[PDB]
Image (cartoon, rainbow, N blue to C red):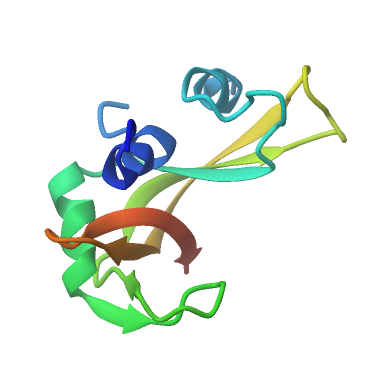
Length: 121
């Protein structure tokens, strides 16, 4: 692959360094390329903490596959949600910071996060 699954996950979902946050980040992370990705979550924890979720609580994924893991700890995340029926090329998002357990799908060797599945209160 030209972009590994792990690299794709970092691009789509990690932002440990940090109203218009989602508008900027969805665009800069290539999630408004010809289509506005409707929902996307960014995680503000270290990549090592997120990678370690792959050894936490096994749970079923939203698509029904079994390789999803729910974090034992709550994490600082931001949800970006497409708003006002906006369409490419004018994607507008709402920014929602919160603290939730995250659920990720993991794959490979080493076994690392490849998809952000959901968050749980």
